[PDB]
Image (cartoon, rainbow, N blue to C red):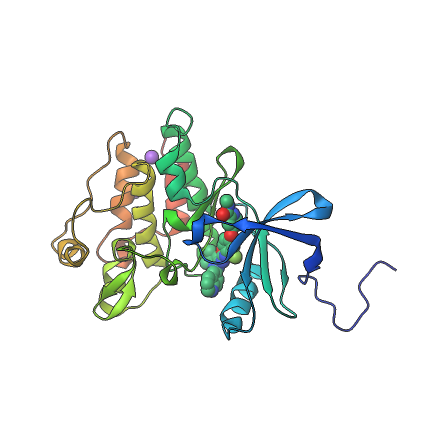
Length: 275
Ligand SMILES: CNC(=O)c1cc(Oc2ccc(NC(=O)Nc3cc(C(C)(C)C)nn3-c3ccc4ncccc4c3)c(F)c2)ccn1
Ligand code: NA
Ligand code: NA
C-alpha cells in the first residue's frame, strides 16, 4: 500500500518545495551552497545548487551519484536531491560550525583543547579508513574540506575547492594544478594519486589540527616545497603535540608511498597510543 509503485520513482529525488532556501554559506568561497530548512522535519540542511543549464550538469549529477554510495558517521551525509529539472539541488546534512580550518582558527582553546584535537583527528582517521575500504581516493584531503558539527562532530567532505579558492592555496606545479602543501611528492611529479597520497595529505591535516589551523610549511614559498621534501625536509613537531602523534605524521610523510601506513593502521595507531 505505502510501497512505491510509479514508473519514474527515485528514492533520492525530493520535493523542492519542502526546502526553504536561506543565505549563501562560506561567504562565496565554498561555491553555490546555501543554508536551508527542510520544513516538515524541523531540520536545517545544506543545499548545493546549480542555477540552470550551464552544462555543468554532468559534473553535478556525478557528485550526487558518488554521495549516494557514501554512508559513514564521519562523512558528509546526502539527504536527497532535486535533479529532474533546474535549479538542481544536492541536499546534505548541515554542519553548524562550518569548515574545520576556520573552526580551529576561531575556536576557544579551553573548549577545543588538546584532547578534543586528538579526538577530531580520530574521527577523520575513521572516515579515511572507510574510504580506503571503499577504495575511494579523496584527492584533496585538508582541514578546509572537513566540516564541524555539534559536540565536536567532524566529517570529511569535498567542496571542489580547486575551482573556488582564490589565492596561494591551489597553484601550478610542472604544469598541473595542486594544493601544493597537501600534495604527496609522487603526485606533484607524476600528477597521479592513490590512497597513499591521501595518507600524505592526512599527515598535513594532522599538523593543521595540532597548530589550530596554521598554514603548513610556515613562510616557505610554494615553489620551494618539492625540492625541500626531496632533501628530506619535513615540518617540525608542533608545540604541545605528543611525540607519538608527531611520529604518525612523519609516518604519513615517508617518501615512498609503500612505507606510509594504511588508514587502517593509522586508526589502530590512535587506538593503541596508550599505554
Ligand atoms: C555551516 N555549514 C556549512 O557550511 C555546510 C555546508 C555543507 O555543504 C556541502 C558540503 C559538501 C558537499 N559535497 C560533498 O561533500 N561532495 C563529496 C564528498 C566526497 C568524498 C566522498 C570524496 C569526501 N566526494 N564528493 C564530491 C564528489 C564529486 C564532486 N564533483 C565536483 C565537485 C565536488 C565534488 C565532491 C555538498 F554538496 C555540500 C554541508 C554541511 N555544512
Ligand atoms: Na594532537
Ligand atoms: Na607510527
